C-alpha cells in the first residue's frame, strides 16, 4: 500500500508483511547483518521480520490508522537468513532499510532506530551485530575524521618509523612539578608523544587549567632544547558539556598540537560535535577506546570489534586506540587485524573470510590511526613491528616509567630499541628470529638498553592468534 | 457507531468522561479516602475560572513557559483539619452550593508524606451543562 | 607511604598493597560492589585487589618513580569479598575509593575510572556491577533530577490517578495533516499525553521545525476545545550537540510543557548538560531508555537494573522510561518494583533481599517518575493499576491506535477504563478480581469500551514474577 | 463562620471595604482635608476605565514592565484652586452625576510639598453595583 | 547613600526596633530633604540637601489590631506596614484575616480623616467597626490581650 489501507483489527504475520527473501538492494539502501538466537518456540524468520517491522513501523494491534502512512517501498525489509555453523539455534539475519526512513546523517536517530529499538526484545535470547551497509550518501552526511591519516602525516612534520610514546601512570594524583619533571625527562630522553589518563587531568586540589600551564612550560622546552618534534596528548575528561567546552576553548588560546578525549566513552554526539570543532580550528583529535568486557567482548549477545571499528570511524577521529596486548584490551591476531584494516584503509570489497558481509562505497573516506598501548616492552618489539610496521603510535605502559635509572634513560632505552628495530627492519631482517640477536647486539653500548634487557628478561610473549572473548 | 464529541458541554477534567458520582458514592468514597490517610479540602471555582485559559499571556513577555490560567480553585472557608466527618463535609457542600449558583464545587485532598495534593471527584454546579 | 618510596623493580603483590579486609568506611568514601568470575588460575582476592589497583594507580612494571605520587589514604582499597550462591567461581567484590582520587561530580572521570578502565581485563571472564555507595557530598555535586516528583506533582496542575497516554506509531514517515489529525483526535478524546518516536521527529522531507508548528496549532486547541490540561511529549532526537541545542532553543521560544529526549541513549553528559538547561528554563524533562538486551539484561557480565536506576537518577530526569511489559523492555515483578522504588523514593537503608549492598545518604534527593509503554490494553489495566497504583505515565501502543472506530473512541475507551479502574480503586475493590466485572459494567454504555473489549478479548496476561535476562 | 467573597460587585479600591460615606460626611472630610493644607480635585472615570486592565500590553514589546492601564481618572472642569467651598464640590458632584450616568465619580486631593496626589473617597455612580 | 525605594524599619517587637527615640529620626533621615543640623536630634553634620530622593519606611509589624491607632497617630501615611500577627494568625483563614486588617486600616484612616483624637478614640472606633465586620470582631477576640504602644528610650 502507498497509503489508505483499511486493515482489519489485529496483527498480520511479520513474515507476510516484512519478509522478502528475493530482495534486490538499491545503492542507497541501508543494510544490517545480525547474529541471533531466538527464545524457544520462536521461528527465526518471525524474529527477523519482527525486528525489521519494529525498527521500521511498529505495532501492538493494527487497524486502518496504520494505513495513514505511506508503506510501499518506504518500509524496512527482511531478506533470506542463514544458519551459523557453530550453534543449532544461531542464525544470521539480513535486514534492509530504504533511504527515506531516517534523518540524513543523524547519529542518535540512526543509533536509536538500528541499535536502540532492536537490541531489546524479551523473546530474543541473544542478538549480536555482525555488519552494516552504509550507502555513500549517508557516509558523506556523516562528518567522519577531521584530519585523518593522509592529513596527519604531512601535518605532524615527521614520519618514517612508528611514533614512540608512553602512558603516564600512576593514575592517582601526581603533583604538577613531579609530573613536569617526568614529562620533560622522558620527552628529552627520546619519546615522541606521552599521554594522560582520566585521573591525571584534574584532581580535587589541582585544576586541569594549572596542570596545562605546567605542560605548556615543559612542552616549549621539550621541543626547544631537543631539536626534534615531540609533544603530549592531553586528556581533557569532564562531567558536563559546558566544562568540556571550557576545557576546549582555554587550550584553543594557546592552539596546542594533538590532544585526546574519552568523550567517545561519554557519548557519540559529544565526539561528533568535537570533531566538527576540531575540523573548524585546524586541530588533530585522538579517540580513546574502552569498556572491552561489556561492549567488545559480548560473545554471542552484543557488539563485536569489526562493527565497533565501523561505528567509531563513522563518528570519526584522527587517532584511535588499538589494543593493549595484555591487561585491559585485547591482543589477538584474528581480532586486531580486521579491526585495524577497517580503520586504516579505503576501497575494499566484502569478504566472508574476514567476517565482512557488506561493502560501503569507498573512494575518499579518510583513514584513522591505531594507538597501541603497550604493556610489555623490549622482547615483544620484534613481533609488534613485524605485525604492524609503521602503523602506531606505540604508547608504552612498562617502558620509561618502569626503568630504575629514571625517565631519561628509560625513554632513551625505548628510543634505542625502536631505532635498533627500525634499522633491522631497514636491513630486511627476519624479525621473529633475528630480533633477539638485534637486541643483544644493540645492548653492547647502549648501557640504557642493557639495563632495560636485564630488568625485563622475563617477558617473552608475542600474541595469541584466535579470539578469547 | 461511533460519533464522539462533547455536545453543549465540555470535559471538566478527571471523572467527567464517566457518569457523574452520586452524593452517596461521594460520601462513601470520602470515608474511604479518610481511612487511607488522606486529608480532604473543599474547593470551588467560578464557571469561567474552572475552564483552562491563556488570555493572560497578553500581559507577560515570555510565554508559554509552563504558565497556565483559569485552573485555580478557591478553598471553602477551612480545610478538614482535626475533624474528618462526612456529614460536616456534606453540610459544607450544601452551604457552598447555596452560596454560589455560578461556581463549581469540588473535593480535593492531600498526602502529607511529601505534601502532594490530589484533585478528585466531582465538578458540580446547580446549573451543570448537558450530561454525556 | 605518603610519597618517597624507593620500590624495587617489578610488580608487588596486589594483596599486600590494595587489599584490606578489616576496612571501616569514612563518610566521604565512594564504594562499589561488583559480581565477578576470574579466568581459571587467578585467585579472587588477587582479581579484586588488581581491579582496585588498576582503577587507582595501575602498573605494568613498578619502580621508584611510582614513589613520586602520594599513596597512603588517597588510593583505592579492596575490602573483604564473599561467594555467590548461584555459581561456584562467582564472588562479590567490595571496593572502596577515597574522595581525593576523583574530580568533584566529574561524570566522565568517575565513569572512566570505575567502569571504563575496569570492565576490560583479559584474565577476567565476567564482571557485573551490583551496587554503588555515593557519599552525600558527591550526591550533591551531581545535580540530580531538574523537576522531580514533589515538583512535577504541583507543576502538572492535576493528580490523583495515573497519567494516561499513547505512543504514536507507525514510526515511519506519517505526513503532517494525518499526524495532526491523529494527535488532535486522541488528545481531545481523553488522553493526557501523546508521545513521538525517534523517526517521527525528523525525516528527509519533514523537518522537526515544521512538525513542531503542526503540534503548536493542534496543542493550543487540544487544550482550548477540551477544557482539561493535556500535552504532548516531543522526541527531540539529533545527530550532533549543535542540532540538540538548536532543537532546545527553538522550543524554549514557545515554552511547551513536558518533552522527552533519547539524548540519554546518545550519552550521559549530553543529558547532564540538558538537565541543567531544563532546570534553568523551568521546563519538565522526560528521559528515554533503550538497548535492554545489551545493557539492562547483561546476566553475570555487565549492567543490571538497580545500578542502571541509580546511574540514571544520578544524572537526572523528571520522567524516566521503563517496561513495555511485552516486546522490547521488561515486565517482571522481581525486576520492576525495586527499579521503581529506587526512582520514586528517598531515605531508605540497604537490604540484600532487594539486592542493595550500599546506602547513598539520602535526605533531599528528588523522586523520578516511571513511564511504561504498554503494548497490551484493556484487561491488563486492573493488574497494572493494582501493582503500580498512581505511579505511571502509562503510554499505550495498542490502545487508541488499534481501535477500528478511530482515535477519539480509542482514546475515550482508554480514558473510560482509566477512570473506571480509578473509581474501583476509590471504592476499595479487590481490583485483581473485581476489575473484569468493572470493565463489563462500564461496557453497557461506554459503547467505546464495549468495542475495545470485543477487539481485545484475547489478551489476559498479568506479569511474570522472576527476572528473565 | 466565615464565608468571604465579593458578589455582584468588586472592591473598588480604598474605602470600598467599608459602607459608603454620606454626602455630609464627604463634605466634612473635604473641609478637614482643606484645613490640613491639601488641595482637592473632582475627577471621574468610565465604567471599564475605572477597573484595571492589562490588554494594551499587546501593543508594546516589553511587558508587564511596571505598565498599567484603566486606572486613570479624568478631571471635572477645574481643580479647587482659589475658592475651596465643599458646597461647590457637592454642586459639581451633582452636575457630574447628571452629566455621566455610566461613569464613576471620585474625589482626589494633593499635598504640594513634594507634590503627591491622594486618591480618596469614594468610587460612586448612580447605577453603582451591589452593597456588601 | 547606597539607595532603595522602600527600606526596612521596626518590627515593633521581636527582631528589629520599636522605640520613639530610634524610629522617628531614622524615618526623618529617609523621608525628608532640606533641613539643617540640630544637636537635640543627634545631628552634627548637614549634607547639602536640594534634589536628594526620599525613601519609604517598611515596618513589620508583629502586633495587630489595638496597636493600629497608636501606629497611625505616630507615623501617619508613612509605611508599608507588613503584619506578622495579622492575616496568618486569623483562625477563619487568609481572606477574613486580610479583610479584618483592611477594615481596621480603613476604619483608622476614616477616624484620621474625621480629625479624631486617635490614641483615645481608636478603641471605640474598633468597637464601632466590629458590629458588622465579623472578621474584625474575631480579630479583637483573638488579639484581646495586646494593648501596647511603643517604648520611648533606646534599649540597645
Image (cartoon, coloured by chain):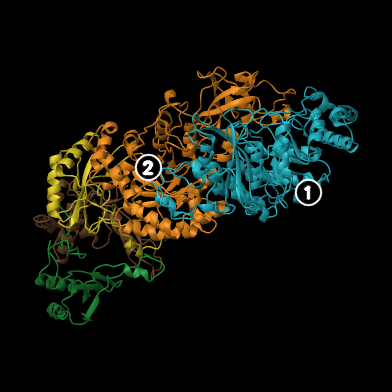
Chain colours: A cyan, B yellow, C orange, D green, E brown
Q: Give the letter of the chain under mark 2.
A: C
Task: Note whether C453 is above or below D74 in the view shown.
Answer: above
User: Do the residues under discs 1 and 2 have CB atoms within 8 angstroms?
Assistant: no
Residue in the foreground of this view, choosing between A469 and A246: A469
Residue B52 position (above or below residue A76): below
- Expressed as whole percent of the image width and height from the top left, the position of residue E151 reads 24, 50
Q: Position of residue A210 (x, y in %)?
A: 65, 44
Q: Position of residue D59 (x, y in %)?
A: 37, 71
Quarter occupied by residue C163? top left
- Cα separation between marks 1 and 2: 56 Å
Q: Position of residue C160 (x, y in %)?
A: 29, 42
Relative to C433, is A16 on the left or the right?
A: right
Q: Is residue E120 left or right of residue A80?
A: left
> Which residue is label 1 attached to?
A153
Label 1 element class: helix
Same chain for mark 1 and mark 2? The answer is no
Residue in front for this viewpoint, E83 or A279: A279
Residue D50: name its quadrant: bottom left
**Residue C244 at least partly seen:** no
Q: Which residue is mark 2?
A: C394
Depth check, front residue: A407 or C244: C244
**Would residue C344 be seen by someone viewing this image from the given angle?**
yes
For mark 2, give the secondary structure. strand
Amino acid at each position: 500500500t502507498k497509503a489508505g489501507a483499511g486493515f482489519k483489527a489485529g496483527v498480520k504475520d511479520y513474515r507476510l508483511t516484512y519478509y522478502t527473501p528475493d530482495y534486490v538492494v538499491r545503492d542507497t539502501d541501508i543494510l544490517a547483518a545480525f547474529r541471533m538466537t531466538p527464545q524457544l518456540g520462536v521461528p527465526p524468520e518471525e524474529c527477523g521480520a519482527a525486528v525489521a517491522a519494529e525498527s521500521s513501523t511498529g505495532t501492538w494491534t493494527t487497524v486502518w490508522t496504520d494505513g495513514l502512512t505511506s508503506l510501499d517501498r518506504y518500509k524496512g525489509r527482511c531478506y533470506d537468513i542463514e544458519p551459523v555453523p557453530g550453534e543449532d539455534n544461531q542464525y544470521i539475519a539480513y535486514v534492509a532499510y530504504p533511504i527515506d526512513l531516517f534523518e540524513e546523517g543523524s547519529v542518535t536517530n540512526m543509533f536509536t532506530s538500528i541499535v536502540g529499538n532492536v537490541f531489546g526484545f524479551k523473546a530474543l535470547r541473544a542478538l549480536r551485530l555482525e555488519d552494516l551497509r552504509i550507502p555513500p550518501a549517508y557516509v558523506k552526511t556523516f562528518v567522519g575524521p577531521p584530519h585523518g591519516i593522509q592529513v596527519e602525516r604531512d601535518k605532524l612534520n615527521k614520519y618514517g618509523r612508528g611514533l614512540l610514546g608512553c602512558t603516564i601512570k600512576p593514575k592517582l594524583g601526581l603533583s604538577a612539578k613531579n609530573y613536569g619533571r617526568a614529562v620533560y625527562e622522558c620527552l628529552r630522553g627520546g619519546l615522541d608523544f606521552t599521554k594522560d589518563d582520566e585521573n591525571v587531568n584534574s584532581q580535587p586540589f589541582m585544576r586541569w587549567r594549572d596542570r596545562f600551564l605546567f605542560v605548556a612550560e615543559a612542552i616549549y622546552k621539550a621541543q626547544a632544547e631537543t631539536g626534534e618534534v615531540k609533544g603530549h596528548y592531553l586528556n581533557a575528561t569532564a562531567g558536563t558539556c559546558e566544562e568540556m567546552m571550557k576545557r576546549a576553548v582555554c587550550a584553543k588560546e594557546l592552539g596546542v598540537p594533538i590532544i585526546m578525549h574519552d568523550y567517545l566513552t561519554g557519548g557519540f554526539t559529544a565526539n561528533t560535535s568535537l570533531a566538527i570543532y576540531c575540523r573548524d580550528n585546524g586541530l588533530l583529535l585522538h579517540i580513546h577506546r574502552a569498556m572491552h568486557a561489556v561492549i567488545d567482548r559480548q560473545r554471542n549477545h552484543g557488539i563485536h570489534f569489526r562493527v565497533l571499528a565501523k561505528a567509531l570511524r563513522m563518528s570519526g577521529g584522527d587517532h584511535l586506540h588499538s589494543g593493549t596486548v595484555v591487561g585491559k584490551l585485547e591482543g589477538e591476531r584474528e581480532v586486531t587485524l580486521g579491526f585495524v584494516d577497517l580503520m586504516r584503509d579505503d576501497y575494499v570489497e566484502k569478504d566472508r573470510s574476514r567476517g565482512i558481509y557488506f561493502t560501503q562505497d569507498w573512494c575518499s573516506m579518510p583513514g584513522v590511526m591505531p594507538v597501541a598501548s603497550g604493556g610489555i616492552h623490549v622482547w615483544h618489539m620484534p613481533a609488534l613491528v613485524e605485525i604492524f610496521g609503521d602503523d602506531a603510535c606505540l604508547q608504552f605502559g612498562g617502558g620509561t616509567l618502569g626503568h630504575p635509572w629514571g625517565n631519561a634513560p628509560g625513554a632513551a632505552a625505548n628510543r634505542v630499541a625502536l631505532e635498533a628495530c627500525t634499522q633491522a627492519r631497514n636491513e630486511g631482517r627476519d624479525l621473529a628470529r633475528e630480533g633477539g640477536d638485534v637486541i643483544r647486539s644493540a645492548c653492547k653500548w647502549s648501557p640504557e638498553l642493557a639495563a632495560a634487557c636485564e630488568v625485563w628478561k622475563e617477558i617473552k610473549f608475542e600474541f595469541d592468534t584466535i579470539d578469547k572473548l | 457507531m461511533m460519533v464522539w464529541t462533547p455536545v453543549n458541554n465540555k470535559m471538566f477534567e478527571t471523572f467527567s468522561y464517566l457518569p457523574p458520582l452520586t452524593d452517596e458514592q461521594i460520601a462513601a468514597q470520602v470515608d474511604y479516602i479518610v481511612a487511607n490517610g488522606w486529608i480532604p479540602c473543599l474547593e470551588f471555582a467560578e464557571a469561567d475560572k474552572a475552564y483552562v485559559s491563556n488570555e493572560s499571556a497578553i500581559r507577560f513577555g515570555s510565554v508559554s513557559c509552563l504558565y497556565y490560567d483559569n485552573r485555580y480553585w478557591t478553598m471553602w472557608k477551612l480545610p478538614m483539619f482535626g475533624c474528618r466527618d462526612p456529614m460536616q463535609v456534606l453540610r459544607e457542600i450544601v452551604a457552598c452550593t447555596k452560596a454560589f449558583p455560578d461556581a463549581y464545587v469540588r473535593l480535593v485532598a492531600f498526602d502529607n508524606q511529601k505534601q502532594v495534593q490530589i484533585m478528585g471527584f466531582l465538578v458540580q454546579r446547580p446549573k451543570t451543562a448537558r450530561d454525556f
